[PDB]
Amino acid sequence: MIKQRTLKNIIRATGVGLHSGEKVYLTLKPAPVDTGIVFSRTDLDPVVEIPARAENVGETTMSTTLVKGDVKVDTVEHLLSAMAGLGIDNAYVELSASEVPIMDGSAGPFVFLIQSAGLQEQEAAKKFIRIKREVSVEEGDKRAVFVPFDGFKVSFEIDFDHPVFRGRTQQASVDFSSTSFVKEVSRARTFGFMRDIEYLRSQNLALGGSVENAIVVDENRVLNEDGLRYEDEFVKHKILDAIGDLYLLGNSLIGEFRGFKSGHALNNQLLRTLIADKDAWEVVTFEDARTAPISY
Ligand SMILES: C[C@](O)(c1ccc(O)cc1)[C@H](NC(=O)c1ccc(C#CC#Cc2ccc(N)cc2)cc1)C(=O)NO
Ligand SMILES: [Zn+2]
Ligand SMILES: [Zn+2]
Ligand SMILES: [Zn+2]
Image 1 (cartoon, rainbow, N blue to C red):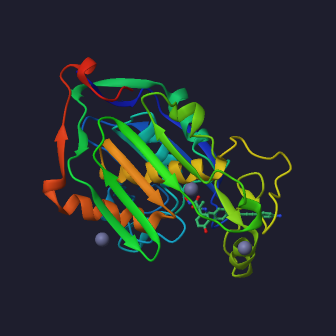
Image 2: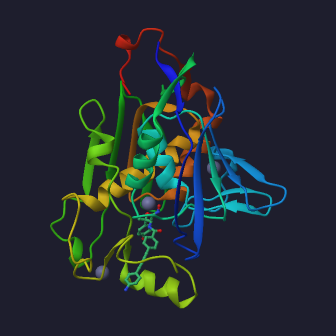
């Protein structure tokens, strides 16, 4: 059978919050079967736990924020993207502040931590959510869709008209039958438009952002000296972001996500809309791994 997966060891890192600019301590820990990913604010007294589930998402402007009452954990999407990519079902994530550290802007540092912690198979079947019917949500010209697919595929199209994007692919469809999340998606850095970052900074926001943790473009050029990690890094990051949001379903997906100019708000609307319609999905397990359309 395909088994649930957790970490073998506790592991730690530090970094700064993209929004706050202040140092945060991160800890990833093993967790029992059927725990899911649970975030804990260990700086608070009492300590506050927030399960990484779609129903606990509050704000979704630019980042995905988990909320419980007045307590928040911001910017969960890149870490969760790594958890999803490596098929980690169960883990505890401890944080000394209200935001996951931005690290290098990608999911790579989290992939690194999870792999370094080691992968532990657990004595319970891994559950998957299989999409049975296509479901979509829209806002203006933005669209996010789940489509049935015998495997796991994430497709995305961005549609920027600024000169710096002219001639760029702005589209990718990744079938994880033959694409490595680790090698080909996880290291895509977050990006921002210079004018938008200036606006954030003018309000004392985005204080942790730098060219060392984000690709910054003006109307016409990429500001980062070293260029891009992947030829299509921008759309790959959107794919990364979508995989992280997808993991808030609480189980790995058998299906396809398609994004069109979509962001965290629409991604989360899609999750809640899917979850609510039981005719459109089912939970499956694989007692024989060789018969499965995915592999971890
Ligand atoms: C990628 C993302 O999805 C997104 C969402 C909306 C959008 O319009 C574009 C990108 C969205 N991006 C961010 O929220 C984002 C990305 C970059 C920054 C920044 C910065 C900086 C800086 C800096 C640069 C130069 C100097 N000299 C100093 C400081 C802030 C936030 C994302 O990745 N969310 O998961
Ligand atoms: Zn423009
Ligand atoms: Zn992102
Ligand atoms: Zn909704």
